[PDB]
Amino acid sequence: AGRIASFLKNAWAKEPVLVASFAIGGLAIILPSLSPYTNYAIRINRATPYNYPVPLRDDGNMPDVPSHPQDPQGPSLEWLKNL
Amino acid sequence: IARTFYDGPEKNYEKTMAILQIEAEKAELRLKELEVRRLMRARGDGPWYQYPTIDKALIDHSPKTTPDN
Ligand SMILES: CCCCCCCCCCCCCCCCC[C@@H](O)O[C@H](CO[C@H](O)CCCCCCCCCCCCCCC)COP(=O)(O)OCC[N+](C)(C)C
Ligand SMILES: CCCCCCCC/C=C/CCCCCCCC(=O)OC[C@H](COP(=O)(O)OCCN)OC(=O)CCCCCCC/C=C/CCCCCCCC
């Protein structure tokens, strides 16, 4: 714990470029696993409608599927407007 | 000499019968296996000579952004 401090000081005094590069790379590696907004990025990617949504045939037993785009059923994007 | 070193003729006789039966059955089985191999390789309708085809489980049965696939 004491020799590595001297090593870090010497690296900062002799090769600052490599010190900055390693610090930036380590932050870029480890930070995304600790962020709560990564799942927000996943949801935003999933909410982009590239293709046409093909309707399902009504068999009379799907109360979770809306009968109209403005019906209360189906997914909501209200979380996206507050972001 | 006969009593001390040898057996009667019936032992050799019947052992020969058993040996002949085994060998004849083996020859018939060899010929049958050759014929079965020929038929199976010609028709491909048996367990042998089954060559792989594409797995149908790899197909995606989803709407494809176009109604006509
Ligand atoms: C008495 C004088 C007048 C007559 C003389 C006759 C001469 C005969 C003696 C010479 C020996 C003949 C050759 C031996 C060949 C026989 C080998 C074999 O086939 O026999 C076996 C029998 O084994 C015997 O032990 C054979 C022993 C003979 C070996 C010869 C050794 C002689 C070496 C000399 C040493 C002398 C001293 C040395 C000083 C250093 C069969 O085993 P088994 O699975 O049951 O068969 C089933 C049949 N049954 C049911 C009838 C029993
Ligand atoms: C608050 C603390 C900050 C903590 C930051 C993280 C750790 C920082 C220290 C880690 C290592 C720092 C640099 C290495 C130690 C000092 C440099 C050294 O070893 O000697 C210098 C010497 C170069 O000098 P010369 O060319 O030989 O000079 C010849 C003329 N005289 O270095 C070398 O020999 C090898 C250098 C290898 C460079 C690495 C290649 C690039 C990698 C960086 C890109 C991004 C990395 C991100 C991924 C890693 C994530 C952890």
Image (cartoon, helix red, strand yellow):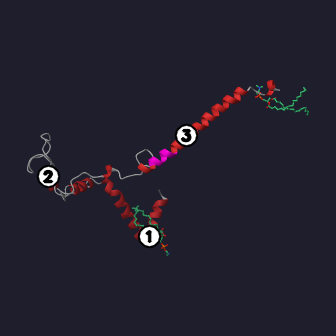
Circle nearer the N terminus (2, 1): 1
x%, y% of residue A1? 47, 56
> Distance between the Cα atoms at labels 2 and 3?
81 Å
Q: Work out whether disc 3 and disc 1 sit on a shared chain.
A: no
Is residue B39 within the magenta segment?
yes
Q: Which residues are magenta?
A: B34-40
* Chain of the residue where label 3 is placed in the rendered structure: B
* Residue bearing the label numbered 3: B28
> Distance between the Cα atoms at labels 2 and 1?
52 Å
x%, y% of residue A71? 8, 47
Q: Residue at x 40, y 70 (%)?
A: A17
Q: Residue at x 63, y 31 (%)?
A: B18
Q: Could you tell me what secondary structure mostly forms the magenta stretch? A: helix
Q: Residues within 10 Å of mark 2 (few under 14, many from 20)?
A: few
**B27 up-or-down from A29: above or below:** above
Q: Amino acid at mark 1?
A: Ala
Relative to the observer, which residue lies in front, A1 or A72?
A72
* Chain of the residue where label 2 is placed in the rendered structure: A
Q: Which mark is residue A78?
A: 2
* Residue bearing the label numbered 1: A13
Q: Quadrant of residue A41?
A: bottom left
